[PDB]
Image 1: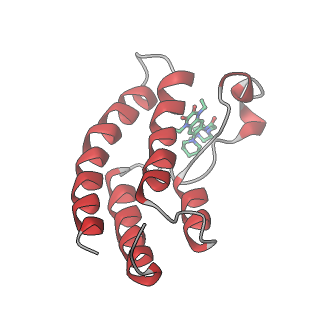
Image 2: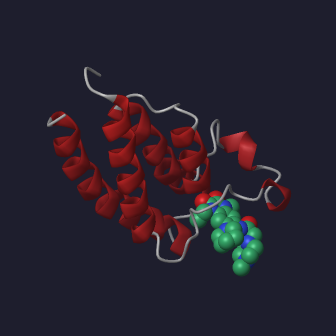
Length: 114
Ligand SMILES: CCn1c(=O)c(=O)n(CC)c2cc(N3CCCCC3)c(NC(=O)CN3CCN(C)CC3)cc21
């Protein structure tokens, strides 16, 4: 965390865009609609989605890379937890984990250069 804030935020914005690009159906773009799943919060302690991540970023809630990555990992893990393995949603979370992990490793390399 020994670096300047502004270049770090620029990197997080770019990284978040790269992660969202992997979600081609935009199914992780907004909060899971709780009005449609009244049991969702019985299973999921902390819902997450890319719009919430963007709000958190601009509110200065991500001041280290690990906190940003942790919220991305919640998007994936919540979806794996709630949805059955035979669903497209579950498989899309697996694919996002794979593609997004690669985006995150490269972004972390860039953060280390700061
Ligand atoms: C099962 C709970 N659920 C998850 O657990 C989850 O991880 N995601 C993230 C992959 C979910 C994502 C959505 N979408 C919200 C609308 C955009 C498409 C994805 C919904 N939508 C609905 O429950 C209602 N939605 C059914 C499809 N119809 C075309 C429109 C009305 C539930 C999700």
